[PDB]
Image (cartoon, rainbow, N blue to C red):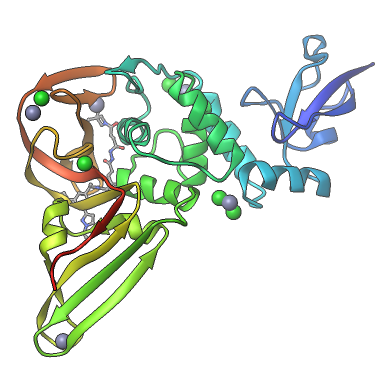
Length: 313
Ligand SMILES: *[C@H](CC(=O)N1CC(C)(C)C1)C(=O)NNC(=O)CCc1ccccc1C(=O)N[C@H](C)c1cc(-c2cnn(C)c2)cc(-c2ccn(CC)n2)c1
Ligand SMILES: [Cl-]
Ligand SMILES: [Cl-]
Ligand SMILES: [Cl-]
Ligand SMILES: [Cl-]
Ligand SMILES: [Cl-]
Ligand SMILES: [Zn+2]
Ligand SMILES: [Zn+2]
Ligand SMILES: [Zn+2]
Ligand SMILES: [Zn+2]
Ligand SMILES: [Zn+2]
């Protein structure tokens, strides 16, 4: 007894296969998945006639197709993606304040905050898998996007997470080649040194939440023994992410794009998303609250940008 099915790694290039109904899928295809569900140790049923299956890349054609779609050669990626997708497809993705959020489940507070942020900054992903899922996420079908985010970050469903580390991984898979940042550090003793950063390092900074303060100057130890001052010289990027350890901060409407609120201890806390629309909105998964002012524990703030040059001589 034999049925005919499709195997794929990208759900674009399908490959017809013949499968013996007396052997498990793993004995003929290796690890095999159906809509994220592991069917490796399952004998083929009759309802599987014509359906499409994801398989781990076992030959060169599937390896090339897998990279062109996911931009990774890690053999385990597809499995971690499918294993995460089996859960994220059960989450609810309500529209909250014109954005796609996530109803709370499996400790996804940080994923919801990252998803809401990604929808408010200008970003193009290099892997076609990410870009396709990015689009479907804006339309409300964010399951594949969240599953891919977990896979690219080497995190699993249930694990707690950091929003800044998550954003950092995603930027590494985004087209930020045009982004440039020139910095200058003035040291009374040693002197002046001007560096330029490209890529992800041009849009992320750890230290202060204020973009204005970064323009004026921040205090940084010099390699000589004096506390030097660093300031921003040029910034060519569509946005900037300013992160700092959680501290009480005042967000003023219209001066920022969005922000991450963190309440709790290191590696054990709750995330909330603050966005600046006509007023200030706070999105906590499926819950929404509005207020004209906001003071609270903020760890990330996102600002819009295009081209900046300093007036400090
Ligand atoms: C969400 C949990 C969830 O879904 N819920 C709802 C519930 C209440 C029922 C539980 C979730 O996933 N939360 N994430 C975490 O709990 C883990 C956070 C984490 C993970 C890995 C690395 C770092 C962090 C983390 O704690 N990040 C925050 C932003 C943080 C906090 C501090 C901090 C807090 N208090 N102190 C004294 C320090 C510090 C830092 C930080 C980053 C870098 N540095 C030094 C340069 N400090 C980050
Ligand atoms: Cl790549
Ligand atoms: Cl669940
Ligand atoms: Cl990439
Ligand atoms: Cl207004
Ligand atoms: Cl802004
Ligand atoms: Zn790539
Ligand atoms: Zn589940
Ligand atoms: Zn010095
Ligand atoms: Zn206002
Ligand atoms: Zn929550």
